[PDB]
Image: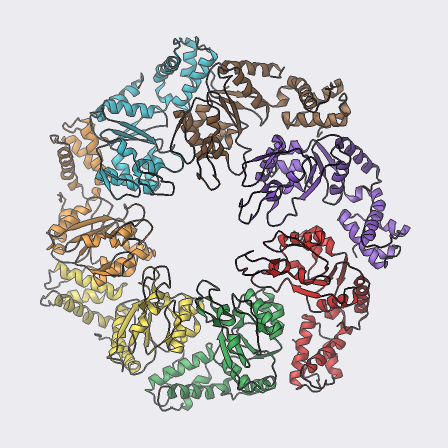
Chain colours: A red, B purple, C brown, D cyan, E orange, F yellow, G green
Amino acid sequence: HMVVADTKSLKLLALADKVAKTDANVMILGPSGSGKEVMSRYIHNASPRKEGPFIAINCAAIPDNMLEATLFGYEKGAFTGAVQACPGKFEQAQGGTILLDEISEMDLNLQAKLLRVLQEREVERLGSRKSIKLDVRVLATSNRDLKQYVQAGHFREDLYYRLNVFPLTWPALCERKDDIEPLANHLIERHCKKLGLPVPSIAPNAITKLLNYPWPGNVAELDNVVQRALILSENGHIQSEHILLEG
Amino acid sequence: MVVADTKSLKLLALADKVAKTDANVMILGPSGSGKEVMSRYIHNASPRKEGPFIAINCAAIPDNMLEATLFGYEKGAFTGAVQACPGKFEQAQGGTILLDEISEMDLNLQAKLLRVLQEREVERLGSRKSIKLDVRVLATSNRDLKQYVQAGHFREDLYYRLNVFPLTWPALCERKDDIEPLANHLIERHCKKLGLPVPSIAPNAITKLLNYPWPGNVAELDNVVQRALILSENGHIQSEHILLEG
Amino acid sequence: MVVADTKSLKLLALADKVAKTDANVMILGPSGSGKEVMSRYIHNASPRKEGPFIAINCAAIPDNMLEATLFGYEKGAFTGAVQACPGKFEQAQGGTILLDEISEMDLNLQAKLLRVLQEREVERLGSRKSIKLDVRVLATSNRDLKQYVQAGHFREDLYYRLNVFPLTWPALCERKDDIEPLANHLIERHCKKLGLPVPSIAPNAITKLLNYPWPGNVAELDNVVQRALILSENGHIQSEHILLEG
Amino acid sequence: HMVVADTKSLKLLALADKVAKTDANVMILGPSGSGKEVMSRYIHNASPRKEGPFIAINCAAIPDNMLEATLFGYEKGAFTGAVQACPGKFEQAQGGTILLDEISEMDLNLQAKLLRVLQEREVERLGSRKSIKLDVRVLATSNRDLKQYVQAGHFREDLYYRLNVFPLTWPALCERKDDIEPLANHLIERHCKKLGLPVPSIAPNAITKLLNYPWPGNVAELDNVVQRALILSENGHIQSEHILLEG
Amino acid sequence: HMVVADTKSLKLLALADKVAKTDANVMILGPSGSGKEVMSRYIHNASPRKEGPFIAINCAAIPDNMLEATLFGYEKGAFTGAVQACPGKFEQAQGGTILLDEISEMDLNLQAKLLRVLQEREVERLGSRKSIKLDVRVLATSNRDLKQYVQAGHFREDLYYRLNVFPLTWPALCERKDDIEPLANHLIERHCKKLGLPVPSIAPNAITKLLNYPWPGNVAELDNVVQRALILSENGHIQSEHILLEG
Amino acid sequence: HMVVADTKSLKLLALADKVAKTDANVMILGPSGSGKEVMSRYIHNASPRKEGPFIAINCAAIPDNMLEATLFGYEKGAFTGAVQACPGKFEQAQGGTILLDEISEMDLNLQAKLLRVLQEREVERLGSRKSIKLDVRVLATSNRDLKQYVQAGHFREDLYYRLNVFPLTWPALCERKDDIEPLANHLIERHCKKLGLPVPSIAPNAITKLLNYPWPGNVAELDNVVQRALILSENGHIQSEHILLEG
Amino acid sequence: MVVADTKSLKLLALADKVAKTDANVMILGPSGSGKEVMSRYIHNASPRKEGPFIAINCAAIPDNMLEATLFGYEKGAFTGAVQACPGKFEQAQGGTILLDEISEMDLNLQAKLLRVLQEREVERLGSRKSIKLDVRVLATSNRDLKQYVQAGHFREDLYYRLNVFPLTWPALCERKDDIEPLANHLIERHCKKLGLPVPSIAPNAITKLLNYPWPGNVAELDNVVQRALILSENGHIQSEHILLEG
């Protein structure tokens, strides 16, 4: 789960705890990453719905234009290709929490649909006129200023406010450098756990080399550098020579 | 309908006058929930009080189903119409219908609405049969309709038919005396909905709310208030709990 | 029907001249409902007064059904033609038809109308059978048709055939002596259809109406009047009850 | 038909009398009007085919793009809409005269078909390979300088030469003011005769008022002014006040 | 057939006699005129195929884009409208001569099909894979510089050289004035014979009037002026007064 | 058969003899002509695949976009028009040599297919997924610089290197004047033999006229001049007067 | 593999360290045969050396069958699919697949590829059934992927998945000590597949080959070599047989 050390991150987890015990929609802003989903589950496991299902969907990763079809579901013959009936992600997240990752990639028409789901607390599959009563807690993320996206006319203003009741800005890695070392060691361990290998120590100069890199790719880039260093050290003591950043 | 500003009370005074009549009411101003509740205020003060109240947001209907929802359709009137379905005008029989954000209707859809208003009857899509209509019409626009007409995006004849009695529900910053009662209203109905006790708002917090221009109006006030309730852990809302934009 | 201005009376005097005949009357001037009441006046003053009077607005028919309603259509003449249907020309047999806003016809629709006027025959879309017509034709336009012809949007041959006896029904500000009698008529017919006793207008209210340029003409006057009746609560309309966009 | 008095118009009828005796194609030039057809009928009744049929078609007045279909005819199913077999206008004008009014409205493809009709003296209906022998004399009109229209590439040069064997330019009404008074009297007469009314006289001042108007609408406009004067005079003596022109 | 008198034309006919005796493809260039296809016929009847068929097709006059279908022929159903099988123009000109008039109107694809016909000396109908063996001599014309047309990418270079073995340029009427008087008389004769009328002569003053006109329409215009003159002269002797030129 | 005399031409035939013994792909460059095919035929007859089939296809002469269809072949119903099965040019060239004349006319997709054919030594018809083992030597031509064509992104680089293993640039006729006279005589020869005529000689002055013309049309243009001269001389002695160049 | 240049030897040394793992390898540099020779080296040095090795060039598949051949497809999944067909991933089960020139995939194919890497399972086109995959992934680009991501033509998330262990296989001029061993190698395999004795390369020819920049790299060297063998009549290759760009 969430492993931090920087004071700004600790403050952000503190806020995450306050909103967790409620049913408010959480908007996780900041650069795109995987932490956002690490917090989403954290919020879930801290919410009164910890035993409920946790469903995640990335609105910027679904090919063949099946974002709409995945969210709301569809009946047999709702569109060219719909060979079967299929429950939406909202249905699978009944009594639990759904995560709409990268929500800023929804077209204006899809937002108008999503708005109705939030308002009516009911969902209807594509090609269906039957509504489904919904008890689902909604989380969402965005790597861009939604307020300006509303101004640009690419996002609904009404939907914007309904989702920004409790925004949390999960910052880049360079703005929380105290998180780098705990995160680095965490990646080393979980990768050693995959292969039954003992976790190796990490050199001081290696750490200093990591702390002083701006990390434009954030956690995703850190995971690469670490995994790369583990290859170089052959799962052994990693030193500054094993740390190859874009420098 | 929670108001307190003297200019808002004047507006409710006008609303009480048209309520007694069957006149088309156009509620102007910025988009919001108020235009929706001020329309239902009129209904409950109208001779059609006990009648049905139908609302439709022309800027919120997905899949281009605005026309199909208003007038209804017969089976197979368009690709996807797998059943018969009455229009919102039919559902508003003997009562009131609200055409929220009416400026979103295309010129063709305006021509159909015009026919409905003048002939007091409606026809479903893919239907030749007219249905006699006894419906009081309310509408809403966040645009200057006259400027919209002159821009050639709105029918002039339809404009005058809907603009016999325009009420302009202003922005929240030009009716600041409504802000404190509104906030307490928003807190209450949110707490009641969640089965929680209603907290009060500290004097400093009120001052903080009154001096914000509210570019998002009521929709933003509900935001701030719901956020404050989370920060206050459902306790009394202090100035520290009110985050506006920074 | 309800005029008092000397230039309006002189126009109705001209209306009686053509009424006796079967000549095509072109009614020019601002887009209004007043044009239809004069065309009714022409009909009721014509030897076809006992015949039918059918009106059609060429700028108010949705779903591109202007051609379909004028000429009629057989079953399956177009995708949607689910039945046979007589045109507006057939219904006006032995009487008078009013082609309101005739400047909205596409050049192709004009060529078909020209065919009807010349041969005194009509044929439904889908049909090759022509129907002998005995119909007197009236038309309107808020547009300089001569200018429209030069702009290549209107047929020159059709123009001259309809411009035998052009009558220009002027704007409301160019016939202000009609304003006061018209205002009382709008009050009377509105109150009567709502079962309310008819109120009169205060002198100050009259002067206020006479000195407004009326960019919306009779359509706008009806708005202001109905608005005043709401404000006056069906009492005597005072100067304060008259809210125009000054 | 025909009512002239101007010296330049009398010469033009004199020319019409010469081609009438022949089978030559006549191109009637000048501004569009009814006079174009009444001279075509004058030629026909002065022609050896005077007992033959006279067929007229306005190429600029046939709706639904039925120009080609009306001229050549069509068998059942030649195009989407052909629910029957139908003879062409050329077939109807067999042994007589056909009038192609405003011929400059034909597309270059339609011209190519008309060309082969003039050359081979045969016509084929749309959707038919069966050719029909034709004994038809051809007349045509145009409000356009066909030579300029040829040079512009909108008209076939070869067709231009077959049709402009004997051009006759029926001028604007202002270039033949001596025709105005006889023409006005003709209109007053035929209207009153159509209603069984006695023909009224026309004041000298009314005549002079008509003579000094340029008539941009030519004969078509004159007919309007005359009718309007009859309406105003109540079929009575037309005076210099029943003549409403422009102002 | 050929009615010439100018030494310029006589030298061309002299050249025509040489190729006639051979099977070489003749390219007749010069302004578009009926004049050519008289030479094409002269070439044919002076050729060893004088008893064979003579088929002429004008590539710029075939309506409804039926150039390719009439030249190659089709089987039933080769295109929308083909309700039967139909031999091409090449098949009809078997053992004789075919004339491809205005060959510069063929699109690059049609040209590629014609090229293959010249090489393989066999043709296949549209919608047909069976190839018909041919023994046809090919003649062609063009009113434009084919070389320039090749450089403009509107004509195949290989096809150009196959057809331009023996190019004969049939000049404008003004560049061979001594042909005018004999041509004029021939146009009067064949027109007067066509209508069963006695053929008249042309006055000397009328002759000189014809000789000093540049003839931009060439012999299509000369045939026009003549037919118009015969109308005015009432089939009598043509005087200069009867000759109305466009100038 | 290759008839040359220029020292630069003899060098290319010397090179051609070296590759003929091998199985390498030969790219013949220079202006488009027929001499490129008679070199392919030469290379074939000098190759160990001499007795094998020689199949030639011009990629710039196949109408109706049937280039891809004729090369690879197709099964019944591979495209709208494929009414039967049909073997490709590669199949017909089994155990022999194929000539891809003007290969620069292949679209990038068709090039990617040809590349696979060269690599895997297999071909499959359109609409078929069964592949056919190939034993075919590939020769190709191009009237343009393939390197610039690759740089222009209109030709695959990898394919360019597979085809330009042994490029031979067959120059224009002006860069090898010593070939003109032997070529011209050869043309006079074979053009006589097809008619059963005795071969005539060509005057010294006439030869000199040939040598000093730049021949922008090369061999194709030379053949025209020769044929034209034979027509003018009536298959007799050719003099400088019979030689009409574009001058 | 040939290799003699210190640069290439260090790259192969790095290849050995990543071979023993299941990490995705990114082989960068100009397009050539050498990339797949390294991808095969990585395989034969990996614990999956006895497993299947599947190669697919994303820039060489005709008729847009890149997505189809990679993922596989059920019958009639697209207009052309007349049969079921397993994808390249299915064929590379328990072994290694090489996605050659991966920068040619469109953003959609990249999204599909991403899910395959994440979930370690694939589903054919027109199929809902997911196939569990034990497949090691190698990839190749002749393009700066980082820049390609910034240009918005490549997914950033997919980029970092593949950029765990990037290896840049340089141009032939940046590793000249490989030229001579590579040259003799190309002669050897070309002569052996043609049933000819292998010729040697003269000292003067070697230096002539060493001082050419090789913009076409190995593909050009193989080209130049094969041409030399023809000129040498399969004899020893002299500098006179080396035709480059003179």
Q: Position of residue A131 (x, y in %)?
A: 66, 53
- Is residue G246 something one can see in this rendering? no
| Identity of the residue furthest to the right in this view | B203
Q: Residue at x 31, y 73 (%)?
A: F91
Q: Residue at x 29, y 25 (%)?
A: D40
Q: Specify whether G116 is left or right of G226.
A: right
Toward which corner of the image does residue F147 lie, by quadrant? Answer: bottom left
Q: Is residue E146 above or below residue D190?
A: below
Q: Nearer the viewer, residue E77 or C202?
A: E77
Q: Specify whether G178 is left or right of E222.
A: right
Q: Is residue G160 above or below residue E226?
A: below
Q: Position of residue E153 (x, y in %)?
A: 34, 57
Q: Position of residue D83 (x, y in %)?
A: 36, 39
Toward which corner of the image does residue D62 lie, by quadrant? Answer: top left
Q: Position of residue F188 (x, y in %)?
A: 15, 67
Q: Nearer the viewer, residue C27 or C45?
A: C45
- Total label count? 0
Toward which corner of the image does residue A244 lie, by quadrant? Answer: bottom right
Q: Is residue F39 above or below residue E83?
A: below
Q: Is residue B146 above or below residue C179?
A: below
- Is residue A210 something one can see in this rendering? yes
Q: Nearer the viewer, residue D171 or C178?
A: C178
Q: Specify whether A201 is left or right of E22.
A: right
Quarter of the image that includes the C terminus of chain G: bottom left
Q: Nearer the viewer, residue E169 or G11?
A: G11
